[PDB]
Image: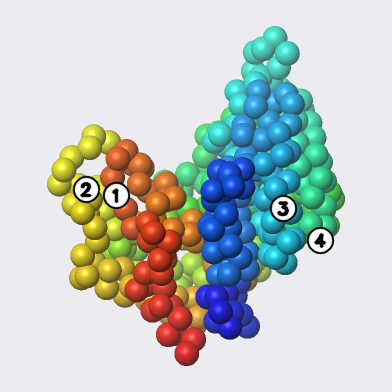
Amino acid sequence: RTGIKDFYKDDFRIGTAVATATLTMKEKKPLLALIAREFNAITPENCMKWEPLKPQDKDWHWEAADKFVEFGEKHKMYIVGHNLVWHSQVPKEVFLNESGGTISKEALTAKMQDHIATLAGRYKGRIQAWDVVNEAVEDDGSWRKSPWYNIMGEDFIAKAFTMAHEVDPKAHLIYNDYNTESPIKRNFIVGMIKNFKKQGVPIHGVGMQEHLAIDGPSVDEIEKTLIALADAGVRAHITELDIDVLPSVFEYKPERDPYIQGLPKDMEEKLAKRYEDIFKIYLKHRDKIERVTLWGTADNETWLNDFPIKGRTNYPLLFDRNQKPKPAYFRLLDLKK
């Protein structure tokens, strides 16, 4: 019982996000060992996305992704495949023909299916969960006007899952999305999910990205999302969990980056209290959740350091800039003691 994964077995798997640099650099070895000690599930940050894996939709770059999957099997990880079909980080050449004007519905369908057949096929039986479709719902309670939707309709989701289930029938198919605590967006998602599953579409689970803030959203809305998803027939997945502790709502300002010198004790405790309250709800509905994954291991590798404002110093994860366990981490351990 050494890592946080051992404390949370019999409940749900504790995962993290693995960067490409961690796999292709020998000086990032301590990070790899740190992940193997603490987590029992992994998710590729970028190496399995369309553009980084297949730039201009031409030649594949399996190298980075292969080292990821191999690392997972080397430690018996719950390997998650990140993004088969996403609206972002996808080459423009995909949504256009050989002219190239706007591609047709049938031709684009072939591109999506060929991509799935190749990507999911290469790691068939070696990947436990796939992020089939991601962020298909607009935050205003409607369909996202992506090229995927505007051309193939909304049924591109139904086809992506169907194709993936044919390619790798043992993989747990997942629909991922953010802002799932927003009722108007959550209702649209659950409704969409229920409609597809009724039509035979193999949707096994729905992923909550859980890009939460230090203040909100509340644990009540988080709980309601868990209940709504459970009643939808799918399994709950926490996919990209992180806690933004910086003032939000861009241009850099000395006042909106007030923790350059470090994170104060009252902030460390407010963050510890935050993570604790969230996991309290997770443990309450442990039978609904299959996996809880934090988007990164240490604070130095978070995307929130440079987004939405570049140059800031953020503390969203369980480990700090020096790979040391933060009070929030131990706070989560005490829950299972």
- Residue 226 percent across, percent down from the top left: 52, 70
Residues at circles 2 and 1 in contact by the CB criterion of under 8 Å: yes
Q: Which residue is mark 1?
A: 313
Q: Earlier in the sequence, mark 4 or mark 3?
A: 3
Lateral position of residue 179 relative to residue 22, left or right: left
- Residues at marks 3 and 2, CA–CA distance in whole angstroms: 37 Å
At horizontal 54% and vertical 58% (from top left) the residue drawn is: 30
- Measure the C-alpha gap from mark 3 to mark 1: 31 Å
- Quarter holding the N terminus is bottom right
Q: Nearer the viewer, mark 4 or mark 1?
A: 1
Q: Position of residue 267 (x, y in %)?
A: 23, 66
Q: Residues within 10 Å of mark 2 (few under 14, many from 20)?
A: some
Residue type marked 3: Val
Q: Amino acid at mark 1?
A: Thr
Residue 82 shows in this picture: yes
The residue indicated by pointer 3 is 69
Q: CA distance from mark 4 to mark 3?
A: 16 Å
Mark 3 or mark 1, earlier in chain:
3
* Label 2 sits on residue: 257
Q: Which numbered mark, 4 or 3, is in the foreground of this view?
A: 3
Residue 274: tell me if it is visible: no
Callout 1 crowding tier (Cα within 10 Å): few <14, some 14–19, many ≥20: many
Q: Earlier in the sequence, mark 2 or mark 4?
A: 4
| Mark number displayed over residue 170 | 4
Between disc 2 and disc 4, the foreground one is 2
| Residue 258 percent across, percent down from the top left | 18, 52
- Please tell me whether mark 4 sits on a helix, a strand or a loop: loop
